[PDB]
Image 1 (cartoon, rainbow, N blue to C red):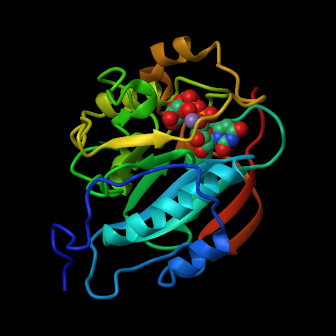
Image 2 (image 1 turned 120 degrees about the vertical axis):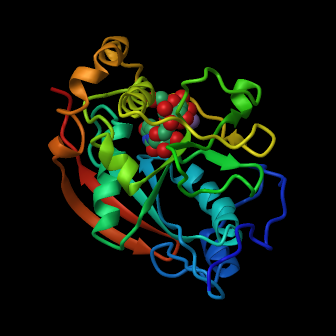
Length: 271
Ligand SMILES: O=c1ccn([C@@H]2O[C@H](COP(=O)(O)OP(=O)(O)O[C@H]3O[C@H](CO)[C@H](O)[C@H](O)[C@H]3O)[C@@H](O)[C@H]2O)c(=O)[nH]1
Ligand SMILES: [Mn+2]
């Protein structure tokens, strides 16, 4: 009973605004089919896409409210078999987005047999439901036309915002790097990994792949990392030593809310 290649539920372009007062109790009420932990499976058909949506997180509860409010209705319309994971970095030291994503990959798999992983910033919302949050033949870059970049790719190798890699694709590159502390460069490092393992980047066209980013200031412990340019230069040499095979972390707590699973983790500090 495979789901059609094109979901009959799709509406196309949508209005994304951040003025509305969002209330998770309401969102839960509006999305009665999504089960505890932000889990949903199509009732009338079998989706071949089993996706874990991973969101790196720390002190972004308000953005998260909006992300849930908008994506859950969307993800259901995309007829996907998915789960939402909020990887909350414990502590107040330097942020590490890429490491958190690795954690989400490992932790999601202990939950369900996901075959697909969508890594998404907490403040990015898609403007057209045809921009499917699933995996493809090649690593997929989803937020390809961001509002802050005038709805245009900043550079052909840009892989930030929202992306998706199948389980096999993620594994072939030894996951993402764990050694990028602070803002920047990890996406470029990941792009090097893909290219070096002979993969290419798949992208929806700019018409259907626009996203809005909730406006925000920079975070105190997520300052640009001055070592990024250098790390990008040596991805080839370091990728096999820094990623899944070297990932260490400690799960401090797990809470399953009706709309997502929150996993608080201690991922160490820069050293
Ligand atoms: O204190 C923090 C810092 C970061 N984040 C998470 O990290 C992502 C955000 O980084 P920012 O939004 O602060 O910065 P950018 O808007 O400049 O994000 C862009 O640049 C980053 C560079 O490191 C990533 O590549 C990201 O994927 C890309 O969209 C967030 O959306 C959120 O999911 C938190 O939750 N709390
Ligand atoms: Mn942002």
